[PDB]
Length: 67
Image 1: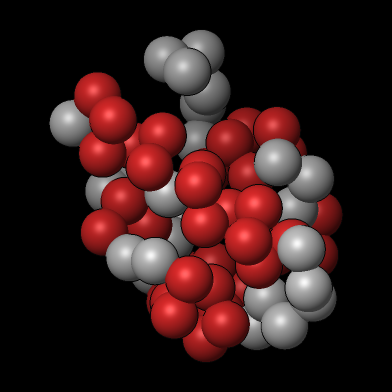
Image 2 (image 1 turned 120 degrees about the vertical axis):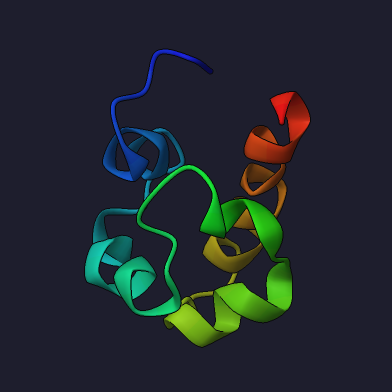
């Protein structure tokens, strides 16, 4: 996944239109901070939406995978 420009291009691949300013509060606006959390953090950013919360759960690993 080294073809992304910013968290906007990454969250876009997982369908996160209503998760922009939401990730800015927790600090997931780049390829690093968001690569150090789990499902407990998704519920904090405001991802109460079911399914969507578990979707980014495996996405957070896309960063630690190559890191």
